[PDB]
Amino acid sequence: GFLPDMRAAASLDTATFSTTEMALALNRYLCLAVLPLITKCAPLFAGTEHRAIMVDSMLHTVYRLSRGRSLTKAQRDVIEDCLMALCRYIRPSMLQHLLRRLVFDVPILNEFAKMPLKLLTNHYERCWKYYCLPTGWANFGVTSEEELHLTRKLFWGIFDSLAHKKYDQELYRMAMPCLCAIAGALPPDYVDASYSSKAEKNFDPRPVETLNVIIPEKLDSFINKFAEYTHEKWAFDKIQNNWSYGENVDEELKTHPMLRPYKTFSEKDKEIYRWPIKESLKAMIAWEWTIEKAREGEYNPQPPDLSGVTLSRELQAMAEQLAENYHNTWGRKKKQELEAKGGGTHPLLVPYDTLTAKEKARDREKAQELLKFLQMNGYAVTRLDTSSIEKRFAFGFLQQLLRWMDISQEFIAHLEAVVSSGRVEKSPHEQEIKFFAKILLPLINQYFTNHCLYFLSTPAKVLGSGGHASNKEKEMITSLFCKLAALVRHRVSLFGTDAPAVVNCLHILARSLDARTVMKSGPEIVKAGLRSFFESASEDIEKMVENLRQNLTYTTVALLPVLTTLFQHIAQHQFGDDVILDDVQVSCYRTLCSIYSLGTTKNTYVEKLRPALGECLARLAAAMPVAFLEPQLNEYNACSVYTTKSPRERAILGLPNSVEEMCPDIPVLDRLMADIGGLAESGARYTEMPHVIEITLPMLCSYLPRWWERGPEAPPPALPAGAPPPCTAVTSDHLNSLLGNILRIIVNNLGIDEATWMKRLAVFAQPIVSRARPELLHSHFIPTIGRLRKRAGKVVAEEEQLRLEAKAEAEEGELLVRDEFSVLCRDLYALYPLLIRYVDNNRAHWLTEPNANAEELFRMVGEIFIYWSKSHNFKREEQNFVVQNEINNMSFLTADSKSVQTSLIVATLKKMLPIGLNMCAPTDQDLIMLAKTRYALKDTDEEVREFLQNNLHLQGKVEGSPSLRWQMALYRGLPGREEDADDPEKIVRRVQEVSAVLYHLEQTEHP
Amino acid sequence: DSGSETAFREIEIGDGFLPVCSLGPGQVGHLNLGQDVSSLRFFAICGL
């Protein structure tokens, strides 16, 4: 009933019957009773693969009901909601027919064509792994070749249609997500078999006009021979099918009813079966294919005609074009009869380059058989070369981006010309500008975001699911990057609204780039353009430093972030040696001198921009492949310009044959250490000297790690390579001093309000604090944390006094101590990450051999955690500091490189907890639990000590349990453990400390 | 990838659990269930 009646409604859809009273009655009946039930049962509609047959027709009729006319907007909404909810809970397997029927209406981009794109984008957003990953997505499986071809064609259809159509805000806004979803779903390296672009065109296949032109008959000896040979080979097919040739008409004989031997074969069928051969040959000669007879000679066919042998690619392509002619002629003659109804279309009425091979097989076999018949006899016919790399989706997409990029550079040059001279509003290419701005940039952004891994992978190193990208793709990507860099170089001021999109796209394209293979044997044009990119960037940085003493907005908005990310990517992928060399080396060195020359400047602009320059020069030091400092041994380094160039080539490059002379502003690395140590000893504040802290500390923290492994401290794996003295002679003592200096600075500057760069200095020192000497604990960890705990206890005492007093003055003081707790939170969050690194690095050694300093630090952090747990002010100010400065991000970074409040427990009672847990004997756990019970009764520290003294005999016995047996065995087997810990005083101290730690930790978990 | 310390979680107890190890061709490995803490290494780091 349901499906037959909705068949009936879809049939009555016709405009002649659309206005029928009971037709509207059927429409109301469906949209009010049947369709809502289908939407409700849609979650259960899942699976049904077995019954997919009806499901298919049911999908078709729901789509046709949505396509019906004489329907209210509410009814249309009901049908569209049914379609959406249905397709949400349907396996992508049976959706191929729906998508194929939709291909007719997807690229029309009419008013009614919006809902199809919404359904398509929802479907491809749901099924992402089904298409990109060759691995089957769940039990749904993997995409078919026809499905991938269809989504490719749909993507290109929307691209071209929306490019040619005039800008519409609604259409662009709603259709761009669909294109993004298709781009994400389609694998970058898809290679469709029929990559040739017909570039034509409902579906009306135009045949080839060949009857008007006169058909040459100089090869009739071949034309008639092949015309009869087709029927003879048909008889050969019959005998291979194991059926004899029949003489008279008979329905039981599927073989030709009058198939008779040539002695008794009537010519009436022979003179009528030749017409298809005539048509094929006439069309073949109608196209630009001249045929010459190279040779001169001449009931079952003795010579066999087959099609399983190989043949020349271009000649087979011509045969493929002739098979396309076969199919389109068949389609024309079928649609001549089919067009009488005006509704629906034949399932195979698709372009030849679009149809799959299984339905292509008949025409392909016919063309190949005719071609073999030509080939063996020796008929020479004469009048593209597309490789698989070109057939890749990424190649065509990148070519389209380059094309629209040159168009974009043209119309933005026109825009600059017209804005410079007056103001011209109606630009001749306004549609192009709006397309490129609104949809093109998000498209490339999303596509490169979802396929960053594919382009970045190399043939040797398969990085990601995709194998690799071709070197030619890897160079056109770099060409595109440098070209958009050239555009933003000047035209940053223009399209300021879209400038954030431009800089985001620049950031994305800075990644997924193998600059190593760009430079090595890369295209000269691309290499020269990118080298000129660094040269222009360096000269721009020089312009800004001279101005500090349009470029200003260009640098700050785009160049510094994007190119800073550039050095970050270079350092991450070890591109420094390959990218930074020769003129690139000179440019970045000039940038270094310019960025360091701003130390004398102390104006508001340089003060506010100094952190950005600090990040930039930290990235310079990270990605910079020569020891700019300690330059006496720069000759040994191969990457140095002096080593790469002969003395004459250095002279022509501008090298004065003295490495120290280009940048005497930056002293030697050793000097740096001396200056930073002296400033730390004198306690220079952030305001007293901003330049050193903001600039030279990034130099140290990025210089020392990168060149430490290749330095003397870490022996090189290749002794012959390391035989020359290292260009950098830093040892472990260098880093240690650096860390100590940094810490000395941190402990000296702690009362400075609004010391915001403390956290960024902690971030930069977070990598360098590791690989640290063990003595650094007793050097600069217990004293600093003890001073911090004194300060915290003082503020907690003020809070306790201010809460025990009750007045408006008490509330105002509570606000004041809330501010004090906030600055305490700032200082403690600044100090903790380095502590985390240190305790993680030294935890195993401390567990293996006990350390009294480590135990004291455990007590210290435990007391701090007690203060934080008891003080609600501390918790609320920690919340405020976290939300204000986004220190939750920094806390998560520290956590993953080892909650918002977890910074107070990982540094006190989670990482270092075993240190304090191991002091107590395994047989003192009874005292520990009893002390915890005292805390549950809320007994003070002295009082719980009293009960430990009274109930010292409540301790466990080694004989009591086998668990205690082996636990006590291990405890006495620990090498550093001694019998002096048996003192009751030590026992009660450790039991009280551990019990308070556990009690307050569980109170923090649950009040 | 998300940073969770535990490889798995919320695992139902059910029938129980047993130690298990599987080795490919040409691969050798030592299994120490923990019969003696003296031979058990890295126990005091995390397990103990």
Image (spheres, coloured by chain):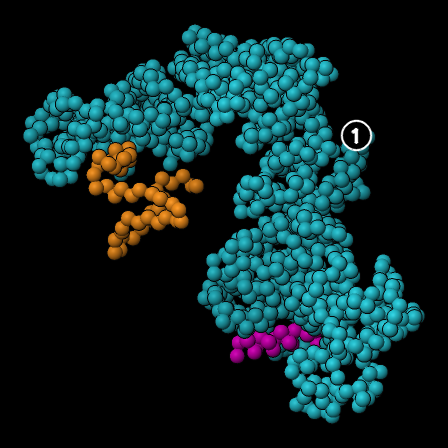
The spot of residue A892 in percent (x, y) is 42, 34
Asked where in the image residue A750 lies, by quadrant, the reply is: top left
**Magenta region: which residues?**
A1-16
Q: Amino acid at mark 1?
A: Ser
In the picture shown, does residue B42 fall above or below A322?
above
Q: Is residue B7 left or right of residue A95?
A: left
- Front-lying residue, A524 or A739: A524
Give the main secondary structure, helix, strand or loop, of the magenta stretch. Answer: helix
The spot of residue A769 in percent (x, y) is 41, 22
Residue positioned 66% across, 65% down in the render:
A357
Q: Which residue is mark 1?
A: A420
* Residue A14 magenta: yes
Quick one: which chain is cyan?
Answer: A
Asked where in the image residue A882 lies, by quadrant, the reply is: top left
The spot of residue A607 in percent (x, y) is 56, 17
Quadrant containing the C terminus of chain A is: top left
Let me know if residue A337 appears in the view: no
Around disc 1, counting alpha carbons within 10 Å, would you say few (fewer than 14), some (14 to 19), or many (20 or more)? few
Quick one: which chain is orange?
Answer: B
Q: Chain of mark 1?
A: A
